[PDB]
Length: 186
Ligand SMILES: CCCCCCc1nc(N)nc(N)c1-c1ccccc1
Image (cartoon, rainbow, N blue to C red):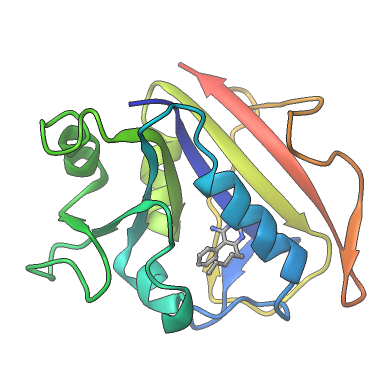
């Protein structure tokens, strides 16, 4: 199994969802960036794993579920089988990471991408080890009811650039945004 990563799009007031919907209007190139980054795997014969909480899974429009070309794993203690269209179910992020070393997935998974939501990000971000955060900064305030956890910059370094990630300001539908990559190893 390869690197562990979080990927998020977040407004200036730290919002990531409004009743699960994006707080901002849909941004086509931001969507394309998310698909490209989470799907691209260099290791021949493997796919990336996407891990998400139950609410994040059901916030994805059905036409976009499962995230194609990736192994889709949902976290839930209430669910007793993977949701329709998903591939795997784990009770916790720890169990999901443990599963990636079981024979059922050990040689199948390259990169692991945590795609939401708030509590899953928080657990990943505060667990020791090597972790990167791919953060799209939506540079406006938007009404939200779920939020990204604080990034502790004592441990997460903002990288000066990263291959395959544009470094300059983007704009869609009149909304400026930018792509950042953070890395910790503790
Ligand atoms: C259905 C795919 C939406 C992709 C655009 C939104 C998005 N952007 C970034 N950079 N990270 C994320 N985790 C998400 C996201 C992915 C799934 C659900 C909610 C937000």
